[PDB]
Image (cartoon, coloured by chain):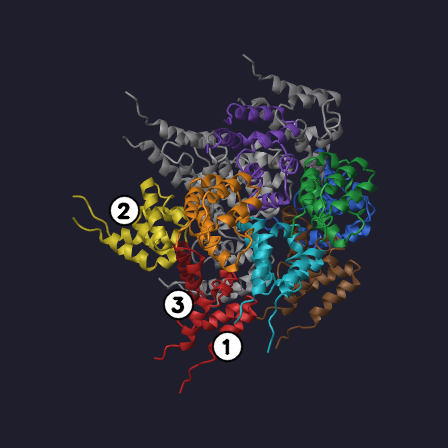
Chain colours: B purple, C green, E orange, F cyan, G brown, H blue, K red, L yellow
Amino acid sequence: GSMPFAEDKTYKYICRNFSNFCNVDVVEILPYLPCLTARDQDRLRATCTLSGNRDTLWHLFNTLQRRPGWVEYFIAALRGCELVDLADEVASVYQSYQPRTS
Amino acid sequence: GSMPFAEDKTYKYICRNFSNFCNVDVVEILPYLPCLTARDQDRLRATCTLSGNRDTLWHLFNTLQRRPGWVEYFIAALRGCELVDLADEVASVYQSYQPRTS
Amino acid sequence: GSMPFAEDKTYKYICRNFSNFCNVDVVEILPYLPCLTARDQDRLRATCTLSGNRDTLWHLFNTLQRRPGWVEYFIAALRGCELVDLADEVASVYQSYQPRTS
Amino acid sequence: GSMPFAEDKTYKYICRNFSNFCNVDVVEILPYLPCLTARDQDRLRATCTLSGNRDTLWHLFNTLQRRPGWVEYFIAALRGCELVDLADEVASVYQSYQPRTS
Amino acid sequence: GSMPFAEDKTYKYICRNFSNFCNVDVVEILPYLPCLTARDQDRLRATCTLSGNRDTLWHLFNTLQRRPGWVEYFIAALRGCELVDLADEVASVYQSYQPRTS
Amino acid sequence: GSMPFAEDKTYKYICRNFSNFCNVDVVEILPYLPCLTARDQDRLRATCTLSGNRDTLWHLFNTLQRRPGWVEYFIAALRGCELVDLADEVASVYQSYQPRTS
Amino acid sequence: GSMPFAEDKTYKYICRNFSNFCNVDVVEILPYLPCLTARDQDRLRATCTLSGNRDTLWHLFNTLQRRPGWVEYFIAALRGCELVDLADEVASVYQSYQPRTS
Amino acid sequence: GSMPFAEDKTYKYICRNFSNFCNVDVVEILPYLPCLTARDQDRLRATCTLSGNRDTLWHLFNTLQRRPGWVEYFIAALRGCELVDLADEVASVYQSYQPRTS
Amino acid sequence: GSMPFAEDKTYKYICRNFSNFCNVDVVEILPYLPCLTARDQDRLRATCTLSGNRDTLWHLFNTLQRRPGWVEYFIAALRGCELVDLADEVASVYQSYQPRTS
Amino acid sequence: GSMPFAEDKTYKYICRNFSNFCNVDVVEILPYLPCLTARDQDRLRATCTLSGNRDTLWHLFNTLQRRPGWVEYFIAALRGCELVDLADEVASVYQSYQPRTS
Amino acid sequence: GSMPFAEDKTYKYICRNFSNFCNVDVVEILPYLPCLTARDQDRLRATCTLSGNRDTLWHLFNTLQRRPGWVEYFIAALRGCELVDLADEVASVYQSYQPRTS
Amino acid sequence: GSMPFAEDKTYKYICRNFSNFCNVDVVEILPYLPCLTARDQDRLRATCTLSGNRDTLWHLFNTLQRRPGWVEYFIAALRGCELVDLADEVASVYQSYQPRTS
């Protein structure tokens, strides 16, 4: 299998420029997330008590889908958080590369 | 045991489109709730001071029955909050699937 | 000790159907209350500024005696507020069960 | 479901230019409102004591129907408050977009 | 000595379907617990800072009695947390097998 | 030294049946407390932001004297909170056992 | 430096017997206060919305000077609130001990 | 920028000796005020319902210009309220210090 | 991308000299804000209950646009709050530097 | 390089006698701070959820400049918090020793 | 050199009856400690993440002075934590034996 | 190949005077790092549980690039952490020597 280069590249981008992604409440990211589960809520709760919002920040991002590809679920949360600029950045870097099923 | 798929599915729905469920006071949800207890009141109080209304919002939903199945107790609170549309959404997604005792 | 099941059961009832208990002024409940203290007045004052009359409503109920058993003090306030129906409801559910000292 | 873009857009408009909507008494908005309930009266009462008329102003608007779509109920209150200009503004922005049942 | 097969079997059950046991606050489990000690409070505190609520969750279960047999103390906490279904599950699997003193 | 068995026994009792001790405001317990210090106020403040009123509840109890023996300081706070029943429970279990200086 | 034992001792006294200090309006304490600043007004405002008058009560006391020694500023407010007895209590306990500059 | 020391100093003075400034109707201060706006009228209205005339008193003072420097607008209102003594006090403390544009 | 140095610089300025920005009601900032949404109203509500007006103050500023660049939306709110001086300060520091699209 | 002995010495002093530094709101220290950044706000937020105000207290002090030398930035915050005594203590111990550029 | 028998003896005592020493916050022990350094703060931080408060408890005790003799620094922290009994225990066992410089 | 003498020399410097580099959160170093990968996040996680922040501190430094030359990536993280002095120290010692491609 070919590891989604866009997911990893977009992963480090959000983690590096996180300072700009911290201008929103975790709500618009975890509960606001279309598909969710109770088990996921408890998971983030643990990370919260772990250290702080920083660990809960990046952790949540990966927690959204618990697997690579959460880029689409992320951009969605942005669309609902009035994050027009942030939505374009993530959607652009991801759209820059995509696999094709033969 | 078979985990209520409707409870989980309906759980994420309310949490995602919570923006529309925030058009009502927590009163119609916690005190207005038919069966309640003092211990429950103190619990939500804690979550209130925790961070804000957001955490108290989703937390309350799960706090209503403290266990899966609060969908019926929720729709009830809606019927008392003049929430006709909200009551149909939750009651529909839940009625879409139900177990049968053989 | 056996927790007064009537107090808890009657507690949730008043909290759920509070919509009907909101047809009276807090006066008939706090000052009108036979036994009272200055400290109690200041307490409710705090809850008032907390959020609104809703929180001050249920809070006052528990504030009346600050402990379980305020059912008798409540029904009394009703008798003085011309609340004949309300007095019968609370007095009935409570009279439905009572402990006996052996 | 498609969130009423007109309701949200009209919501921020009334909230921004509220300075002009404050030229009327809350009466023409809450009691004057065709369909109403006692529970609603107590709700606004709470917000009143919360802080002031400002919070009670915007809160009442959302309290009118407790759900999106109160635009029609609002314009109605305007028609009864001799608010010809205000009625046209709200009725226009809303009429600018409407869903169709296929 | 015969290791309580019910304690171990019930132990893995609670740990596997913990997702459903996470619908309650740790309060109803640690402080609410009938017999407790200060030393126990500090112990769980340590596990809390260890990683998160997950480790503190399962750890607390074993911390309740610090020894096998906490099944009775657990079901008790459930009875006080309005956990009727959870109380039946644990009480059933345990009652399914019990030793007899000859 | 002999660890006050009454303090520990009374400690778990208040923590287990805390549901009944939550019918009072923390004020009657921390500020109302005869001997107090500014440093103590800040301590509880921290626990408040920690999680909620639950942690601040039990924590405050131990914070009252920061050492075993706060049973006398507790019963006092009860006497000032009109807690006649609660005062008898704590004062009884404690009076049930006391050391004697030879 | 030697921490003002009178300030701390007088601090707990006012906080314990606060029930008697609650017989006056916060006005005679904050605005009536000789030296004041706008920044201070906003601070207390925050505490007000925090929980209630209780937190705003003790908080204001410390907010008066934001530092130990507000005993003189407090007794002053009492002199202006017709609080003769209260003024003597605070002024006495403080006068009971005072440092001397060598 | 240099914060107007006269505005702050004069601010606390009016707030402390407010007892003497309460000998006039709010009219001579809000409507009588030369430059005013409808939005300002609604603002004070909110504070009025907030608690009482006390909060509306000091609040109005800051509401007059919503920014530091209202000392000139205040003294004006005094000149129109026959407040000769009050006008001299405020005008003196302010004239005691003034900035110069180089 | 080049992080708006003006937004950050202006951000700390408003946060440091906030004492002067606290001379206005949050209304002129949140509801008065041209473009707004219901979801935003609930967000600030949470911060309100969090601690006080202080946290709600700075939080609101960032909440206005939930992203950098709210300087234009802020200055606007000032223009509507009769804040001539405040409007010039923010508009000046921002106009001091601006990017150009090649 | 020569490690600022004054910074370390003053660091332990503030941390030891912190009990006196806890008489002020974190606002006068973090937002009130002249030069600040959004990234810094999020950092302290994390520490807040970490444990309580205690950790956020000392952490904030070091967070002010994230590097040794924040003594000047600290004393500044004191000057704005009406902390005359506190400002002299920190400014004195620091002025007691200073390096000279040859 | 003669190894301080009192330090070792007192070391095991605090470690054995630690259950009673856990009734205080680590603050009164590490930051409250008169002489401290930044390097020490980071050290304890590491132990914190190591396992829990238990390891951080005993570790901190030895971390206070990083060398034998911290008994005096410990008793000091107790004097500031209102720990009268604890202060006497440690101060007594230590005073029971002391070296003399010939 | 010629082993980067600057990397090794700068490596020991940061490790020796680490006490000053511990005045920043690991966030500004790992996530904030421009180019990053998920695999790297898990690696540091392991070191975290290994012993403490100390091991995670130096380990992270080498983990940033997993190979010599991370000096440029380090100085970058400093520029984003407001570390002006730290950035000059590392950038200077490194710039003191550099290879040239013939």
- Tell me where residue F20 appears, x and y as whole percent: 64, 51
Residue depth check, mark 3 versus mark 1: number of the one nearer the observer: 1
Say if mark 2 contacts mark 3, CB within 8 Å: no
The kind of residue on which mark 1 rests is: Ser
Which quarter shows the N terminus of chain K?
bottom left
Q: Is residue H7 above or below residue K88?
A: above
Q: Is residue H4 visible?
A: no
Say if mark 3 contacts mark 1, CB within 8 Å: no
Judge left or right: residue C95 versus residue E47: right
Pointers 3 and 1 within a single chain = yes
The kind of residue on which mark 3 rests is: Arg
Pointers 2 and 1 within a single chain = no
Which quarter shows the C terminus of chain K?
bottom left
When asked about the image quadrant of residue B73, the answer is top right
Look at mark 1 in the image and give the residue it sits on. K92
Residue depth check, mark 2 versus mark 3: number of the one nearer the observer: 3
